Amino acid sequence: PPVYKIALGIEYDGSKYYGWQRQNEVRSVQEKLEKALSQVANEPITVFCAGRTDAGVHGTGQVVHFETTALRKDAAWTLGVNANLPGDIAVRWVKTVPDDFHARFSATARRYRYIIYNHRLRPAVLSKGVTHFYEPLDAERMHRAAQCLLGENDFTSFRAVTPWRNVMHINVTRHGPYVVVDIKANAFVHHMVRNIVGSLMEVGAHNQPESWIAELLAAKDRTLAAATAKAEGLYLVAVDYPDRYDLPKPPMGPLFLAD
Amino acid sequence: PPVYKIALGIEYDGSKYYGWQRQNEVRSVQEKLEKALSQVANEPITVFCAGRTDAGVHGTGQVVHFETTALRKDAAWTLGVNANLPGDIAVRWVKTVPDDFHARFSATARRYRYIIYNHRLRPAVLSKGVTHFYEPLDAERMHRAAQCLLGENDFTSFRAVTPWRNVMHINVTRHGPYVVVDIKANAFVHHMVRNIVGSLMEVGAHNQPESWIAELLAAKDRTLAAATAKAEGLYLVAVDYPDRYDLPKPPMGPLFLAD
RNA sequence: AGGUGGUGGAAUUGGUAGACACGCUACCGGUAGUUACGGGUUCAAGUCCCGUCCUC
RNA sequence: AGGUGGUGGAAUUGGUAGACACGCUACCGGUAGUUACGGGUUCAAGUCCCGUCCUC
Ligand SMILES: [K+]
Ligand SMILES: [K+]
Ligand SMILES: [K+]
Ligand SMILES: [K+]
Image (cartoon, each protein chain N blue to C red):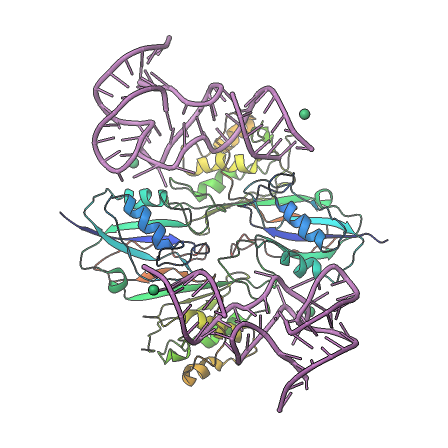
């Protein structure tokens, strides 16, 4: 028998499942995906995702892979799949990927995106999927201050307690009344991202200094900075890989929000 | 007793209710809004909305009004309300509006917005709320051809069978992989909007002539043009009013999608 | 000057209260389990008045 | 050349089938109610093969 390895770019609005990973009781993405996906090969399939993203967390670039003895025409895998998939999980693309690949492992670096309302007045354009902030923010600052964590420092101050991850780019802008964050750090420590935002969103609305970003970073402490950033607003928009593999990689959303 | 009239800009993701208007059995916006809203004055309230928008139809500018003998500090009306409101209905603003006002009636002209995916691959960034199209579209055209219904003609060709409504602006663009439509016609005939899109979306993917827009318009027939446009993708982003009244009017979404 | 779940610690500074972190018991990363009292005003009270009983 | 709910009329041209329109019975704008047959291949068949029985 020939086992075929193929990773696929899946896309999923969180909001309603309890995160990625399984565990007999409730319901997860993987659960959903695993099942459907495997139903289409009669050989019970198990997926290997590249970012065990948890509850109320969205993805639009999450990519997974797996092996099988079954064979398709790139269709069951694309069109097929999300057909047996609940309208909040989709496939985006597929690729006959070389055995030496790994999703979690071949991975080289990630990129998340944080969204936020600001009207002072909870949105209705779907709750779960944005988190809105009250008191008025300041982009110029948000981004202004954050832009220095790219150094590389001890993020031990943002790990919910190797605290040496490498940041490549920060970026905090206000496309509309929303403010949008994005980062492409080599790797990530627990939440972080999230504890970053809070501890950055704080600076946004003032209440804290502009320079303060460098304080707690250097300070090197979690039990100092701002509260972890809600949840319903994270967007894993794509994980970076090597070009040997050559994945298909399209617009990372989460919506019009251009790459 | 002094009855107070006040209209308020409400915002609502459709998707899950069965439209605006009530009727003992199921569940509607108005139902939701009516209730909550009225709970906050102990005088059973009835709303008067300015666009009885139906099932799976979104609003982000829908505005309603009503009268009451109760009195507030602009808070129960804003913050209060959507607190007693399900996360898919929000208030956006309120205004102590002059008795001579009317929501449906004082209205002068409307503006809808249509969204669409195009990946060939159903999105997961919430279904209900977008409708995605298969075969690849053409904005340059979409908008190119539509731009002539602003004349005013017999739309009797788009009324699901006075078929003389006045169009002020059409507009069909591709902010991202989405294509986005918007129109500000004085008034509207049954669906229309919707039957327009289909009969315009057709031109988008070809299958029909570029000039064809003027054909059926002049043709003056419904049982000729393309199928009515899905549903889960309409966005009543604001209704235009007179400046005597002076409403507060903020960004019309539906998201970052800038005014 | 105040008092919130097994603690710390918050509440668009009248609005689904317990966010966010944290601790031990289970159980195949989860899910379960282990607003001081009495009134009052208001459409609503952790937050506002009258009180009893606490507290550095 | 084909055959789909009370009809017309479609199905990312193997994928939750009945979209979109339309007709009469109720009932305080709604909600209810009034894939030709037998097999086969495939993980899946309105759509693909073998068939019976229809059809301009
Ligand atoms: K206040
Ligand atoms: K045991
Ligand atoms: K095909
Ligand atoms: K009767």
